[PDB]
Image: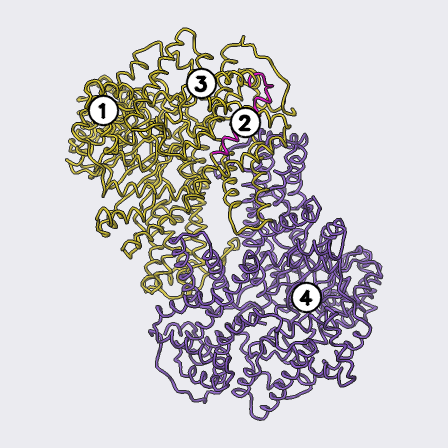
Chain colours: A purple, B yellow
Amino acid sequence: IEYDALLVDRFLNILQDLHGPSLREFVQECYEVSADYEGKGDTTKLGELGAKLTGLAPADAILVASSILHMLNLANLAEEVQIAHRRRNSDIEETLKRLVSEVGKSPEEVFEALKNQTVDLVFTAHPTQSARRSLLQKNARIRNCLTQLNAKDITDDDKQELDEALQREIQAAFRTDEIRRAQPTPQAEMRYGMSYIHETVWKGVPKFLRRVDTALKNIGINERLPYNVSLIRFSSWMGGDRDGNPRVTPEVTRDVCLLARMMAANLYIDQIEELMFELSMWRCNDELRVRAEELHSSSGSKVTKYYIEFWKQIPPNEPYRVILGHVRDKLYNTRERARHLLASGVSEISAESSFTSIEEFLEPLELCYKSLCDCGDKAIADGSLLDLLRQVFTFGLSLVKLDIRQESERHTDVIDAITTHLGIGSYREWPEDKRQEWLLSELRGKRPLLPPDLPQTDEIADVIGAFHVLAELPPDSFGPYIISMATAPSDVLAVELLQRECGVRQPLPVVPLFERLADLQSAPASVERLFSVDWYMDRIKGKQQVMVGYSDSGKDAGRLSAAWQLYRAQEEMAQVAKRYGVKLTLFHGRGGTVGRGGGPTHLAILSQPPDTINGSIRVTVQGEVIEFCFGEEHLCFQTLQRFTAATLEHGMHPPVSPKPEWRKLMDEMAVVATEEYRSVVVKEARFVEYFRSATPETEYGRMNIGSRPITTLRAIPWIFSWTQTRFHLPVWLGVGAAFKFAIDKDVRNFQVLKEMYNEWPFFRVTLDLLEMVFAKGDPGIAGLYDELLVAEELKPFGKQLRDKYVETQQLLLQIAGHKDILEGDPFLKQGLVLRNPYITTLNVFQAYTLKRIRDPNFKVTPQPPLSKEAGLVKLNPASEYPPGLEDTLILTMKGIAAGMQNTG
Amino acid sequence: IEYDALLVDRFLNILQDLHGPSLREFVQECYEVSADYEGKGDTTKLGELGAKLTGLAPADAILVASSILHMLNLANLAEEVQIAHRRRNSDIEETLKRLVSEVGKSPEEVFEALKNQTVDLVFTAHPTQSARRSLLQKNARIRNCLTQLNAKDITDDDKQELDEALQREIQAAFRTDEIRRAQPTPQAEMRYGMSYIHETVWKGVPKFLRRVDTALKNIGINERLPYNVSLIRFSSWMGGDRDGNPRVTPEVTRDVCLLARMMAANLYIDQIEELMFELSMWRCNDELRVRAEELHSSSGSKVTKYYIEFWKQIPPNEPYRVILGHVRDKLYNTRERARHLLASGVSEISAESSFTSIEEFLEPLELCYKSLCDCGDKAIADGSLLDLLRQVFTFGLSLVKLDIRQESERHTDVIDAITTHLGIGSYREWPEDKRQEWLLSELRGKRPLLPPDLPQTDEIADVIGAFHVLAELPPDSFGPYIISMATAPSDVLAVELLQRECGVRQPLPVVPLFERLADLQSAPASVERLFSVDWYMDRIKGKQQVMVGYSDSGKDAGRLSAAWQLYRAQEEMAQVAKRYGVKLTLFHGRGGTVGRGGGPTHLAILSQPPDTINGSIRVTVQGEVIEFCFGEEHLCFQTLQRFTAATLEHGMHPPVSPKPEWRKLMDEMAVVATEEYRSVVVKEARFVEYFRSATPETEYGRMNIGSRPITTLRAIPWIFSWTQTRFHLPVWLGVGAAFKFAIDKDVRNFQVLKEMYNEWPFFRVTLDLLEMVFAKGDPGIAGLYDELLVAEELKPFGKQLRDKYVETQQLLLQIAGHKDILEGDPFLKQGLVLRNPYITTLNVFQAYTLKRIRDPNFKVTPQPPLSKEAGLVKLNPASEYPPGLEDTLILTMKGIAAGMQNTG
């Protein structure tokens, strides 16, 4: 609550210096009026505030909007810092002690479990990130300045300077345009998510483990965690996922996957280069002695004058510096090899001259470790050496594995053209049992099918291309090959074919994507049918993985229905696997907002059926969230902490399995929910009309968050639209009726709901999330958009919804036993209280802007300029909307999303 | 005394945890014992240790030697922390206040003077760094872990993980052979001293400067210190100084001056890259709008796939990023250019393709700074953009300038031979008057001289070739050409010629190096003569530099004499200059030890004739001192602080000019101090034998410190010798007599001696330095080497010096009015008490070790190996001296060197 006033005060001043009191006063007022609204709760303020803003001139409007955006951002920044300081002044050491003590588990059990556990976090570039790298940068700088600013040992002059620092970064950020003017490229996006790896996660992982070691010893286990074990791994979709996005061509993958390999190569060099300086021992293994001597006579060259450190030949007097040096040289060709490959077509540098596999890079390293531990000096080995070893297992030769995605109907096109051409029918019109026949005969065969004279097609080729590249690059640089909207088992085979048929060394594994409601239901079906194919079941080798999507599930049905459906689905799927003895691991397509399956990490894991993780899980970090989770130091350390602590516990101390009673009621409710949902968003004709009216869903594409070039469509904008209007329709629409039903059915059921909310994790967490949403909603604000945009005829329709909101919230609070929303979290409300008034301003602002943009005959009374006098307006060359209107709008969305902490 | 134990304690725990509880104890005992002598004086106990020590197995002798070495080392580490942590609770701001407040100066007068001040700190690689470069890395590591381990906001886990690291690091340095086996190379030496630049000084400079900006504000001036103004500058000798060192071929010169530019260009990139992410405003100069418009308009729309950031074309909406990006590329070439010129022979990268002059590089950067200013974002410009500008004006493209040093005679060798080969006789035999006449006319001629067919010694080449390398390399990468042993005006005119006769664009400026007493006295004349030759005066352009040695200077003549002479030297020289209106600046060849003109920065600059410094001053940093003065960041900041402060005062608050009485008496004691001096080193053949008899001089080389191979000895080895044996004979020799004499010549002089040590800065510092010297010398250890290595013959001669020593020390304390030594510095004495007992033990282990070499028939009763065991000793294959002696001797030196915190 302190830093808040600090960052804000600072900003307000800069504002005044750059633009003069007049304007600083305006922003100052807006807050006041919004306050009276958020405080006394009198709706007259919103209308008054509206008069204040509709008068502003283009430049002032763009400024005013921008001003609130920055203040809001700052708020979030202050909050992070405050959270960090507090909580230091959850934790594995905790969960271990708790598991061993309370739950009582042999430390060996823990240790083992820990060893056999792996949480793969895959970053994805879903258009969920609003801020641009430019501002995200200034932020990390302000965070850092704000921290050192609270240093309890900095002199006077010291502080004085740090302050000046904080201010100019604030001003610099204020001075840059936050409206990304062009759509990013797939390569640019990968360069974004990558920034975190070589800036916070790279040197983070090793530290995280050091703590996981300290913890282990604190529980008795006087043994560090083996460096080969990898508790957490990072994968990426930036460059691999090409579903619905034509811009991710097969070359884009070569480039991004090559560039990433160069970065790793580069990082490790700094590692080794120094490591050499540290391992200056001479007492070595009988084994290392040999290995070293050989490299001594083999090199013989020392003329490397361009080497800053360790230029002339290293004497065998320093055994490790010898091997390390070698490893380094090979590392340079690996970096340069890639450079050329990227720059020109090829490289003079030979394949054998560089590292092409992880084993090739480990053998030398591992050697030093053994040598050290053997010749005594183990501790010296457990130092920087142990850290590097861990990095290699976590990051490997290409910072992160790359997944691949593509809707199967594309694979059908390819396979169909191949059959048509060869004169053997239309694979398309083939019955599933027929396709499985042909496809299985082929997989068993030995004779090539891919005809060289095959008639290509931009897409029929774009897909073959992808596969080829998969063959070019190493086997390790890739993750699984996901098949969007793929149903029948033939769909998984058609890919198994193309992989080998397009020549692929170690064909990557195939994993289906069950997201649409329907697919999630018939999910355990296709799953079993697939384990019934001998060939497959045989090449699979026990290990199997399937991806479950959280976004579209509740888009076509309720949130409640979907939430339960995904539970059931991954619940059964876990048996259809257990029955066929396959280690099925689930890939969770969790978003940023609760509406798309998001929410606190430990809670989300706890809400998953018992016995369906067992130390193996993949989870998506959608764009925006990457910032949230690994933006800072401590932040990253928490995300890693959180994930492994939850996954570990969910295994050795599973959640409760739903009582038969609950299941029945749950299944029954889910129906009511979906019937309630589809009834209004689907069955109601004029709904969509009302939808594209009371919300800025239409203007979503203007922000330019991604590189993807209507009722039945898109989900990110869907969630977004109501998050802006602060209504959250989608997140709760079902729940209203689902509850009233279980009660109107039998009065005693109410006591059941209360029973569930108190004993069933899935259910408590599900409700607990909806409370947070309601805590960020405001039917008042929703009404304003209605009144201003929604037509007269359907005006009353809005009110109905407005009522369902309230009704659902009461029911929600009763079941939970809360007399007040977020009655549980006091600080979470404190924050809101400070924020809300700023958000409410941007709301009213957005509301009237849309009003002006849509109704060109909406008269307004223009006020006199405020800022000291525009090119600020000329920043948007050709705009379809009049003057400041566009930029202003993009700004409001930018900020409202900021204050809310969520884009979509 | 805090870490003083913390560190030592863990060392032992590791020591016994690695070699057996016995060795830990033995080492303990040897201190326990030696602690008694230092606290008693009965040299009787000493003999005991000697017996035991020599009776240790070769392997154990090493271990026991290294232990006391690594221990003593630690003491120096814990002491560096004990100072920071306690000081963190001299200063320019202070000095600026004291000047405007107390001295009554105009804040504008102080600012102005600060803009015209400059302090060139010249790093050199003298064989003074008796520390392994591989060991230094680990010391820094330790210091860092010691500081952090003593924070307050760290947790228990944090503390345990840190203390854990701090040990594995101490164990790392121990498990590493501290004796360098292969002698260094000129390239390896420039590399050692260079690390400090990019590892500390590169970032340090901008910081120190901002602070100065802060100070200037904290006293009035609300304007920053212009970025083009450089308070400090960095220069090197490493690769340019070839005096006395043959191994520095003219190739090594281009070699290092090339590598340096590759590093400079390199560092600049990391900076510029970063600053590209910062400056992201869209507002700019009409000038910059135009400029950036062109760059974007041209240079295609190319993408650089191997570029991590800003790979694609930059939009012109980011003016600053356009220009800066172009600077980055220009930078990448420059970095690649030199990279090639080193490794291969030439480069494809064009001349225009990269940066050649600082102007090319500045022009753009300055364009931005002014653009940001004009457009209101001065506060933004003063951020990272200023720091870079400050670096550019301080490091240039070379990073550090290079001085070239060659003995005067070596230039005669050439000129003499190019006359002998031509018609006219011999230069060498010509009278000085002749030399000037000829050389002058020759310099005014138009017809060549240097004959093609001229024969060439392996020496006449090494000098003429060097002159060619200077022709090739760029003018900005060179300092002056320093003529060691400068004597007469011809000496300068000879290089003035040779230079033009070997073809040089910008003939480096030539500067005399008056180092022998003889030349010092005559110096003022020479300097005036050179100002007399119209030709020279015209090429001088008003400025003039002249170095003055301390090392060899105090060699021929006693310390006192030399010290006084040097004063008069610069005293008159200044007057001469002043007479001809020449901005004479002096280059100070200050050593590391008091014997080579060492001591506290401020004290030193203080003890210099008033009105000789003012504008500028150059100072050397002899190898060992570099680690000192720039080892840590806090060290660097303070060093910069010290110089600029001291230097600023000496200008506005000059010291007192000696009183005629003082002058006279000084001159007198001067001759008396040399008399007693040379009389024992020159006018005595019995001496030379005692030297090689009592001090381990002939062992200096066994350390492979630098690459450089009676009066035939250098300064360093000289002092090194008497410093190990704790006698420091060369530093106090003359003094004793100078005093006694003036005490007899008259009694009123005792009151005049005291009267001087109170009011005259120079006379004070000199004695104060001495007191420290004596504060380290112990005649006990002095004579111990007699009864062990001194010939029974001149055994008394030794005891005769013993009495002069003690007589001198006594009289000193009398003049200073002190009871004890360092009486006025409880900290230091407290340090000797805890450190000495260790140094002693090493002296004991050294005096006997020298005998086990000098006297083969020395019977010593062996003992059982204390450690748990061969290969240790077999680390030195080809060694003349028996088993563990070769190594133990070098070790005992290295160890004592650390104890005394000085070598040469």
Q: CA distance from mark 1 to mark 3?
A: 38 Å
Which residue corresponds to mark 1? B750
Quadrant of the rendered structure where residue A734 is? bottom right
Note whether A576 is above or below B549 in the view shown: below
User: Mark 1 or mark 2: which is in front?
Assistant: 1
Percent coordinates x, y for residue A430 in the rendering:
80, 71
Q: Position of residue A846 (x, y in %)?
A: 49, 80
- Our reading of the magenta stretch's main secondary structure is helix
Badge 1: residue crowd in 10 Å (few <14, some 14–19, many ≥20): some
What residue is disc 2 on? B66
On whether residue B31 falls in the magenta region, the answer is no
Q: Which callout, 1 or 4, points to the residue nearer the camera?
A: 1
The answer to whether dots 2 and 3 both sit on one chain is yes
Estimate the spatial distance between the alpha carbons at disc 3 and disc 4, rounded to whole Å: 74 Å
Q: Which residues are magenta?
A: B53-75
Q: Residues within 10 Å of mark 4 (few under 14, many from 20)?
A: some
Chain of the residue on which disc 1 is drawn = B
